[PDB]
Image (tube, rainbow, N blue to C red; front, top):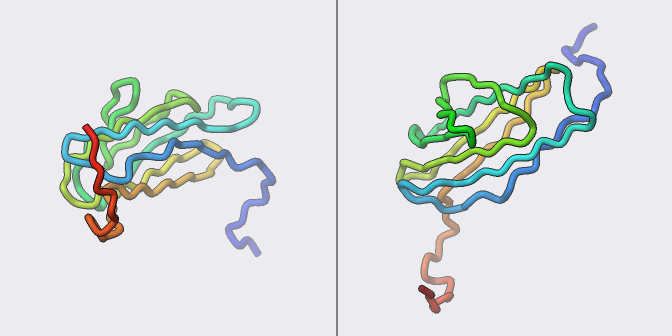
Length: 130
């Protein structure tokens, strides 16, 4: 009848992000390089960024200096954007980022910072460097 499935055969944009630090400290800042791949370009197409943090803390600033609040909603300056996340928690920093496109495509990237595979010293990489 309707199925809530809008018939549009378009190319879903891919955002290439650099592998972020898997462990973070309080005061540590992750440089999230993001490159949005979309052929052509856009037509007054603004992207809207908002992220939910089950953690509770963490300063996420845009490369342009714009401080991003999780409860707020900011427009992206383009396809080439970078995010500087300063982790301010001693927990597992869980940041679920939503990139909303004007055409109605939602791109969510859930980042888990400061994870642990256990076996802290059991992984014998005993040679530490300066």
